[PDB]
Image (cartoon, rainbow over all chains, first blue to last red; front, top):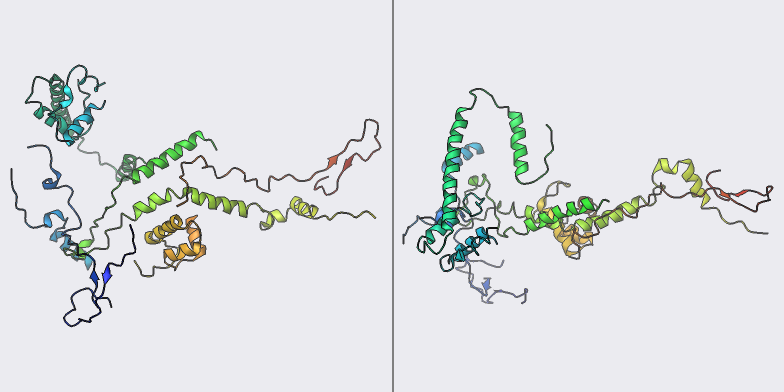
Amino acid sequence: IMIDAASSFVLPISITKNVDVLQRTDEILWFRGPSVIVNERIINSGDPHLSLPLNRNEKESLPGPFVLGLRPSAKFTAHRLSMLR
Amino acid sequence: LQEQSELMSTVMNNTPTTVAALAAVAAASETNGTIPKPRSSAQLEQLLYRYRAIQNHPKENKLEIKAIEDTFRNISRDQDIYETKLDTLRKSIDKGFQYDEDLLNKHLVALQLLEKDTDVPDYFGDPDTEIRISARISNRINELERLPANLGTYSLDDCLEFITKDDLSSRMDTFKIKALVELKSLKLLTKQKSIRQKLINNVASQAHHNIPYLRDSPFTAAAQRSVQIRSKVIV
Amino acid sequence: ENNGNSVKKNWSDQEMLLLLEGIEMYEDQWEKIADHVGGHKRVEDCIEKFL
Amino acid sequence: SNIPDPTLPPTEMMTRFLHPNWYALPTTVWLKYGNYNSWAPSFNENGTVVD
């Protein structure tokens, strides 16, 4: 098992005409494998949809992925933006 | 034989009905040495709820259900004992006491320190006690070496930054660095000991060339003179 | 982080851990420890910090 | 690393220090010649610090 593989490759043809959005060298980086898309970094380790207690076939279409991400209320953020200045 | 943990092993393996600990006088009474009245809040009490709910279907092969249901009466009694005792507590409060803050400051601080087992100041050789020091050091390393590697933080100050769905806020590793400075300094302790051995035994092994009152003492200045006496030549 | 830190003898946990990585890495060569802290710390200060 | 664990039987750090305030100083050397030599120079002092 080696560590020093390249995994980043550049085609010699300069196609930098419509390429202002991708990841450039500063040429285009062409990796060996695809990317990883992660939804949220912080998990909600409580929240009994995930905790599964052992008391008492049901579905629940929860609104989006933002239930499991620990977001603060706008009341405190306004209380903190008043604490800003 | 860990009767309160074999039920947790049967619950975690999702097969507490296929064996159900085989409750007889030879098995249900051997691991107990009446169930031993478990200690946790609900980690060993919700087990007995599912253990009874699973053993409701055999209901006769397991004679220990009477021992479990007797402690169900004792739990409902001592909660009812406390709920009358909490009510007789809340009426027995004097309407004026005016609890002092700086003692409650000394009561909030000393309780928080005594929770997680650290030494509390009052403000109110010998290898026997050398093992009792290193048994607390190795206690700490084995407690730091059971924390998960993906530990992250959340301060109350990130709401001024407006973190998006994928923004990578810079306060995520303010607990992870402090847990590895602690874990690695508890292994380089005999490394700074060797440097401090080489530091003390290099500044103190002379002790009479830099220290002024010792090199200006009568006995040292005579002895440093006496060792430099060259030999007398005969004839 | 890659930026230069504050006035010295402050010893942030980045500087503390990168010091602690090097002694686990090298066990000597305090030139090779001081640049691993970031190079803005002297040889005479990391040993003064470690002891 | 090559560090040992701090739950090792070396955790002593002060065993063979021997400060030079506890060093032995050369003192006077009382000699003995015989039982019936009471006119001999009874001792010897070459570079002794005390009398």
